[PDB]
Image: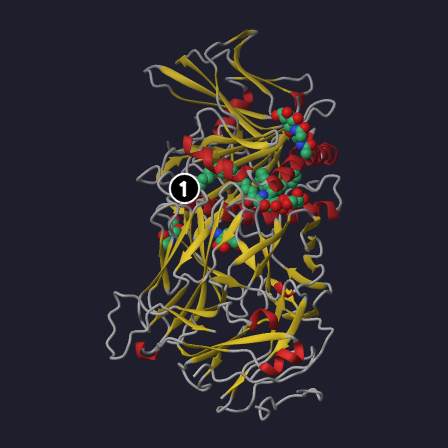
């Protein structure tokens, strides 16, 4: 139930002449590959991005993908030629192909296609098919593309066989990076809340890995209920940032502490009290002309 | 180009086997097919090859596809006079209607008749009605005369179905003064 | 354009005035994928801005991270500006170390 | 079930003259194509369609336009004919759910002539068998002739007892020029029929050689004096 391998493709078609395709690959939440319109070859982003695969095993895939890219571009352009009143430029296609990893190689595979931001077509079993809620005009292009059994045989190999085989290789080749532990660093803050005579207390938490984290404002053991957890925000160095905020009246701040629990911290939870020796000092290094 | 056919022109005796070659560069290479085109006529499909290494036979036509070598071969078993046409090798780059075909330049096959009774005899036909050259030998040929007065055509192969007979024939009009630019048989009436 | 960009400006490390740090501009929920992101120190362009490759979440919404080396001070201001077809005017979001 | 047909078979044009080619097709094919076969060159795509309404440019799209009126019909247009242009145009229809299923028409041969004055029909005279051949071989060889026809657009056939024959028939693959060094010059062509001597001996059997000529229409009102070179049939008897 652990990991999910994703090959994310994004294609833009503005006019007949102008088009581009950019692709990124994610294992868990770590980027493994990068490939852009200008780059003829797929670039590695980790020292273990090739996995267990040979130089030739890899070159088979890269050549098969290079051939696919230019084939995909021209095939979309011809589909717009075919679909004249029904669909027209500009076109945005998003492909999400990969395989979810489990114990004992359960390795579920998926190939999901979005069109103009909406999920429409799924490869399944042996063939393409439109999902519930798809535009009706897609029925014909799917038939046209399903007539190619050669493409189908290649995709079925990629999903059923080549996907799980490749990613297991990555799961070992990059075992160190996947299982690494990075410690969160917390610092307190506050802004005036919308209501007059109220303060919004902010607890920043930055630089932690893996992604599971526990952040709650507290007054002793009693957990403070009005704590609002933010959305996980990515740092450039493959680490995570999160802020948790509590809202209170002015003067009610004393006694409060931002508690943070993380896997990297061992048993030692970061308990950071509001008016601490360190908060006083760290706050003085922050002052500015609001 | 992207699809080369070799040779440009091929000649075989009537009854023999003939081999036609086709090399390509096109990618991807979903399928390869062969067409027969007679003079002043359309293209007729002979065989369609789909697999990595594929073999297909249709009547006297047969073909072998080698996708790895980007190479294909057409065989004609027991060559007839009716096979004196152009042979075109085409490759489709996709397995759906979205794909485009890539056409080879073509190969002219000319079939030389097998005559077992060479009886060279020149005749006259007049007016009419107000000069042939029949039973002429194979291999040897009559070049167009370097003249603008007398008109002489190139050789022609006719065949009677029932009587199992074939012969070369050249015609002359503007008699023994004609047919004089190439090697001529000795025992000619 | 169909979808409007969410913009969030935050720093890698706790801000100490006069100490080097990395400022992150994280843009989310935008469609089409075409976008222009520029980071400004005191209204003027920062040239050494590094872009992460564009990717999309499960809900098909595009995201991207822009980051640059910066030094927080008492008087200097930092923001990232977004030019995207969903909006007629470029959106500008300032770094507020307190919220 | 059906055939892909393109009309006309032969076309006589002039320099700068706007020319139109049509293509009807019975199969329920959505895709239709127009090719030009250059001598010693492979087919090149001009225009193709998916139906309607639809006209997508090929590789030789310059110089031509095309239009699709119906699913069946597909027309190609030549904007301005190159003065000496002699070319073959081919129409092909294909299935949208099967790339392999592709059928081709019989083709269209074009000759751009300057001027309309040059076009004239063939004259046909059949020669009777030689008596020297009768005792020599026990066979009889008839010879059909066509001379003075312009342009190349002709079809020769032999007829016995009002029925067309192919047995013992030979027509030249090439027509001779009546003047070799010219921009436009009349053509000459021969064909032989060889039957058994016994079959000839009684002129009860009727022998005909027939030449189908492809000339002008009836709407293209021509200027000159003598008989108009219309699309006609010339014959000779024995
Ligand atoms: C405007 C309306 C549009 C609406 C929008 C929705 C669109 C509808 C659906 C869109 C889908 C379009 C797909 C078009 C495919 C096509 O353009 C393209 C078609 O070209 C085909 O190539 C195949 C492979 O060479 C050929 O198969 C050959 O067939 C032979 C028998 O004939 C043999 O079987 C042979 O073994 C086989 O190779 C086939 O003849 C040819 O036809 N498909 C191929 O080349 C096959 C490969 C397909 C792969 C699918 C890719 C999925 C995700 C890709 C993103 C990945 C980015 C790269 C990341 C890097 C990878 C990291 C490594 C991880 C390893 C897993
Ligand atoms: C890839 O796996 C799929 C199963 O997801 C196989 O495709 C078919 O799946 C359907 C169910 O949707 C079954 O009814 C069929 O029996 C499966 N097809 C066949 C031929 O058995 C597919 O077999 C796999 N592809 C390859 C190449 O192994
Ligand atoms: C096509 O693509 C882009 C639209 O963003 C533009 O740069 C270019 O000028 C466009 N060209 C035409 C002919 O529309
Ligand atoms: C993408 O790559 C193709 C093929 O190399 C090229 O023709 C096109 O100009 C590129 N598009 C860009 C850079 O937007």
Q: Which residue lies furthest to the bottom in this view?
A: B177
- What colour-coding does the image apply? secondary structure
| Image quarter in which the C terminus of chain A is found | top left
Query: Does the rendering let one see residue C20?
Result: no
Parent chain of label 1: A
Looking at the rendering, which quadrant does residue A122 occupy? top right
Query: Does the rendering let one see residue C71?
Result: yes
Q: Nearer the viewer, residue A276 or C49?
A: C49
Image height of B163 relative to A153, above or below: below
Image height of D55 relative to D202, above or below: above
The x, y position of residue B124, in whole percent, is 56, 85
Assign a secondary structure to mark 1: loop
Asked whether mark 1 and ligand 1 are closer than 8 Å, the reply comes as: yes
Q: Which of D217 and D63 is in front in this view?
A: D217
Q: Residue at x 49, y 80 (%)?
A: D176
Position of A168 with respect to B157 (left or right) is right
The x, y position of residue B189, in whole percent, is 66, 87
Position of A151 with respect to D177 (left or right) is right
Per the image, the residue denoted by label 1 is A83
Q: Which of A95 and B183 is in front in this view?
A: B183
| Image quarter in which the N terminus of chain A is found | top right
Looking at the rendering, which quadrant does residue B168 occupy? bottom right
Q: How many labels does the image show?
A: 1
Q: Which residue lies furthest to the top in this view?
A: A222
Q: How crowded is mark 1: few (under 14 residues within 10 Å), some or many (20 or more)?
A: some
The x, y position of residue A94, in whole percent, is 50, 37
Position of A55 with respect to B35 (left or right) is right
The x, y position of residue A84, in whole percent, is 37, 43
Q: Residue at x 67, y 69 (%)?
A: B165
């Amino acid at each position: 139930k652990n990991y999910t391998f994703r090959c994310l493709q994004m294609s833009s078609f503005a006019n007949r002449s102008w088009s581009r395709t950019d692709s990124v690959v994610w294992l868990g939440d770590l980027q493994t590959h990068r490939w852009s319109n200008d780059s003829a070859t797929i670039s590695f982003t980790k020292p273990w991005s090739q996995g267990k695969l040979s130089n030739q095993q890899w070159e088979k895939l890269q050549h098969m993908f290079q051939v696919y890219r230019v084939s995909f571009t021209r095939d979309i352009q011809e589909l717009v030629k075919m679909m004249s009143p029904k669909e027209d430029y500009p076109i945005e296609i998003q492909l999400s192909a990969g395989c979810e990893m489990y114990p004992g190689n359960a390795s579920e595979s998926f190939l999901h296609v979005a069109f103009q931001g909406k999920y429409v077509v799924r490869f399944w079993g042996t063939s393409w098919q439109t999902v519930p809620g798809a535009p009706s005009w897609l029925d014909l292009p799917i038939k046209v593309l399903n007539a190619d059994q050669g493409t189908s045989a290649t995709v079925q190999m990629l999903l059923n066989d080549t996907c799980p085989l490749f990613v297991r290789g990555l799961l070992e080749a990059g075992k160190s990076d996947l299982e690494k532990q990075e410690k969160p660093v917390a610092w307190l803050s506050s802004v005036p809340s919308s209501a007059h005579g109220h303060r919004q207390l902010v607890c920043h938490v930055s630089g932690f890995y893996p992604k599971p984290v526990w952040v709650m404002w507290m007054r002793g053991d009693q957990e403070q209920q009005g704590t609002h957890r933010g959305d996980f925000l990515p740092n450039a160095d493959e680490t995570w940032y999160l802020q948790a905020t509590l809202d209170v009246e002015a003067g009610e701040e004393a006694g409060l502490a931002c508690r943070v629990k993380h896997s990297s911290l061992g048993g030692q939870d970061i308990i950071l009290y509001w008016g601490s020796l360190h908060h006083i000092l760290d706050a003085q290094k922050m002052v500015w002309n609001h | 180009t992207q699809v080369e056919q070799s040779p440009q022109s091929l000649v075989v005796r009537q009854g023999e086997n003939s081999v036609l070659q086709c090399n390509y560069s096109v990618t991807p290479d979903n399928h390869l097919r062969w067409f027969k085109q007679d003079t002043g006529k359309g293209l007729v499909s002979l065989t369609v090859l789909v697999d990595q290494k594929d073999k297909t036979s249709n009547g006297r036509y047969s073909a072998t596809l080698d996708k790895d070598a980007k190479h294909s071969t057409l065989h004609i078993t027991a060559t007839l006079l009716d096979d004196t046409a152009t042979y075109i090798c085409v490759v489709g780059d996709r397995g759906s209607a979205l794909g485009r075909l890539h056409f080879g330049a073509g190969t002219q096959l000319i079939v030389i008749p097998d005559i077992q009774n060479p009886d060279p005899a020149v005749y006259q036909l007049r007016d009419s009605k107000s000069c042939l050259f029949t039973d002429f030998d194979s291999q040897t040929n009559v070049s167009q005369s370097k003249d603008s007065d007398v008109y002489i055509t190139d050789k022609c192969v006719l065949d009677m179905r029932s009587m199992d007979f074939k012969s070369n024939s050249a015609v002359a009009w503007s008699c023994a003064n004609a047919f004089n630019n190439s090697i001529i048989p000795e025992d000619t009436f | 354009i169909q979808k409007t960009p969410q913009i969030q400006v935050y720093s890698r490390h706790p801000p100490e005035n006069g100490k080097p740090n990395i400022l992150n501009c994280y843009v989310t929920q935008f469609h089409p994928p075409h976008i222009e992101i520029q980071m400004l120190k005191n209204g003027k362009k920062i040239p050494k801005v590094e872009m992460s490759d564009m990717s999309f979440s499960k809900d098909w919404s595009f995201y991207i991270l822009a980051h640059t080396e910066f030094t927080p001070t008492e008087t200097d201001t930092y923001a990232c500006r977004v030019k995207h077809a969903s909006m007629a005017e470029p959106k500008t979001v300032y770094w507020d170390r307190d919220m | 079930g059906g055939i892909i047909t393109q009309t006309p078979k032969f076309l006589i044009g002039q320099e700068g003259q706007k020319l139109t080619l049509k293509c009807q097709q019975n199969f329920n094919h959505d895709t239709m194509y127009w090719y030009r076969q250059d001598s010693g060159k492979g087919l090149r795509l001009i225009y193709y369609s998916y139906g309607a309404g639809s006209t997508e440019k090929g590789d030789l799209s310059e110089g031509y336009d095309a239009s699709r009126e119906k699913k069946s019909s597909f027309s190609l247009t030549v904007t301005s004919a190159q003065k000496n242009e002699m070319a073959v145009f081919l129409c092909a229809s294909g299935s949208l759910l099967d790339v392999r299923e592709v059928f081709f028409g019989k083709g269209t041969r074009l000759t751009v002539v300057e001027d309309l004055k040059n076009v004239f029909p063939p004259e046909v005279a059949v020669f009777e068998p030689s008596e020297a051949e009768i005792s020599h071989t026990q066979k009889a060889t008839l010879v059909c002739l066509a001379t003075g026809f312009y342009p190349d657009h002709v079809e020769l056939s032999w007829w016995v007892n009002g029925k067309e024959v192919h047995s013992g028939v030979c027509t030249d693959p090439q027509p001779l020029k009546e003047q070799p060094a010219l921009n436009d010059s009349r053509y000459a062509l021969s064909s032989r029929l060889r039957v058994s001597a016994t079959f000839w001996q009684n002129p009860r059997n009727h022998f005909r050689c027939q030449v189908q000529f492809y000339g002008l229409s009836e709407n293209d009102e021509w200027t000159q004096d003598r008989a108009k070179p219309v699309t006609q049939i010339v014959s000779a008897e024995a």
